Image (cartoon, rainbow over all chains, first blue to last red; front, side, top):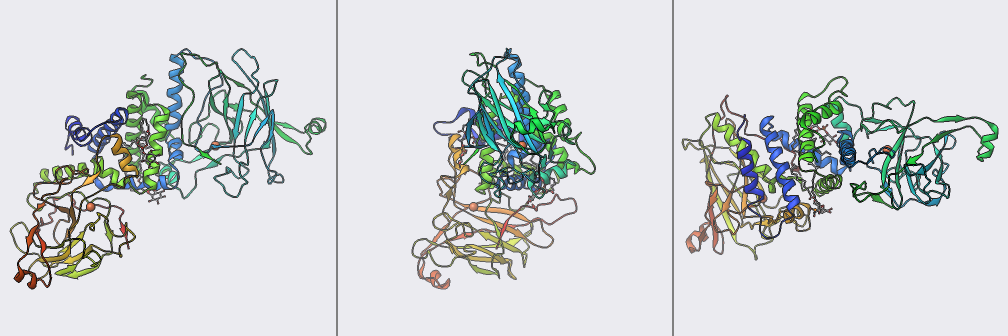
Length: 309
Length: 309
Ligand SMILES: CCCCCCCC/C=C/CCCCCCCC(=O)O[C@H](COC(=O)CCCCCCCCCCCCCCC)COP(=O)([O-])O[C@@H]1[C@H](O)[C@H](O)[C@@H](O)[C@H](O)[C@H]1O
Ligand SMILES: CCCCCCCC/C=C/CCCCCCCC(=O)O[C@H](COC(=O)CCCCCCCCCCCCCCC)COP(=O)([O-])O[C@@H]1[C@H](O)[C@H](O)[C@@H](O)[C@H](O)[C@H]1O
Ligand SMILES: [Fe+3]
Ligand SMILES: [Fe+3]
């Protein structure tokens, strides 16, 4: 079933997409298109992919884009994690060491969250009778432990049902999304609720493909972070919580050593009173170490389309 | 910038998408996913594709799917034509010869058009003062010239502005879309209007990428055909009209020898009266030769999602 070799494929892709050019071309877009189309044609030949198969593939991609699920598909196939593996290797070749490890953004960041200094309450209290209270705190430092004041700590996470605000229109706008600027001691504190892990929408396109692959679409509980400061490399990270069934079986492959936190239980009446609470809560420490931005450093920032509100 | 070789890539794709499988897997979908993801990761390494670039690519695909333009993109990059090049080579290796040549379907077929025997008027007359009348006629035969009665001739084409019904909601439903069953003499006749060639939606995603490639998004005038009959291989084809600026410069590469027709001019008062018209018209002959369906023959039918009404 090999009807064309790669030479013949390359000649056809050139005739159709390069020889037809008139006037100015974006050379990078041209290069990438030619490469990816040649690779697709070769895979069609090697695997003898039939026209009905190609159309099913394109229809699936159309449906995924219509459901706004291609971000989730990038995560679940491991493409998003792969970009981080490449970034870590680039940084190693640059001699960049130290710093809290990176991991994936995921597709659910929303720009425009409430900003405050040193402290934020993340939740609206609508789940207070059905989920544990969580306090998260940490210090943001450079690699020698010097505190960083005014670092921008952006956090977002799921509610007690595994749902995120903005996407879940039942939640108040920006629920469980805050920006916290570190205080004079490099500290941030968030008063919030325990996140639960979650799966892909069960009738959606991402889970439809995972089902064909025999795979689950679940993530362990986690809290997402962007951390930035003048003079420092921007960090995209998370923590995961020890004890989760899916901790080392995340469908998006985001868990790493260095990013697992233990949720401690605080039942002590004195400490509860000190925090102005009425019941036991969970506490997580998550300190963040940022690497100073050097002239030689590859960028740690990523341009990506993100929701805003 | 090579951070991973293909061995390392293959091992990662396997860890993420194969080792994670539990219970039954669709082996074909698994095979194709593993191949395409490995090829994507390798192209990312070879071309040093940055995360911002990957996200732009996925955002473009999302936007294309939302605008229902991935079919048009498949046509414009030459993927749709490439499937026909493969089908023609498969048929040659099967010893299938003769028959009117195939070409691309395009993305604008709609199922459920009015059916009639031997004759159809395709247009609603709403453009009668602004476009030329066209009569199309032909005989459908086997490869030795024997007529075929009751062959299903499905035709669709653009109006005087280059727009298709269903997609252009201003047109009456099924305007310029008919199914004509061949009569006792193997004949079909369509009374219609001259199609004009057309381009991609100028502010749409397909033209946005073509612009980066320095390419136009125009097709020459044409009329699309499905032809089918019991005992015969289904045919997807078109004719193009001689004289079109874009005849041999179609952005979808669909023009072929054997499928260019000449539009003759009929100004003769006697002939005009015979056809029950009042003014000169254009006439096209387009005969169709179908190949008999043999046990050895590869399928000439393609499963594809198509609009219906
Ligand atoms: C550009 C790539 C090349 C494309 C062009 C070449 C692609 C070639 C693909 C060959 C496919 C083999 C199919 C064999 C038989 C199919 C039978 C079938 O059941 O059809 C469908 C299966 O077809 C697929 O899902 C294939 C998609 C894989 C391609 C994308 C991954 C590529 C990886 C990397 C590239 C970068 C990709 C980017 C990474 C983010 C079933 O539908 P569905 O239940 O899976 O989803 C269903 C579904 O389809 C419903 O219609 C929908 O309503 C519902 O919501 C959804 O859940
Ligand atoms: C799965 C493939 C891998 C993907 C994952 C890997 C992809 C890697 C791609 C790298 C891209 C290089 C970009 C370099 C710099 C980008 C700058 C820029 O201006 O961004 C944009 C350019 O990015 C692209 O268009 C790249 C798309 C190519 C990928 C698809 C073809 C693959 C071929 C075969 C595979 C089968 C494909 C199937 C064939 C059908 C500009 O936006 P736009 O004006 O082109 O369109 C605009 C636009 O983007 C607007 O936002 C929108 O509103 C408007 O309508 C639209 O017109
Ligand atoms: Fe998340
Ligand atoms: Fe057309």
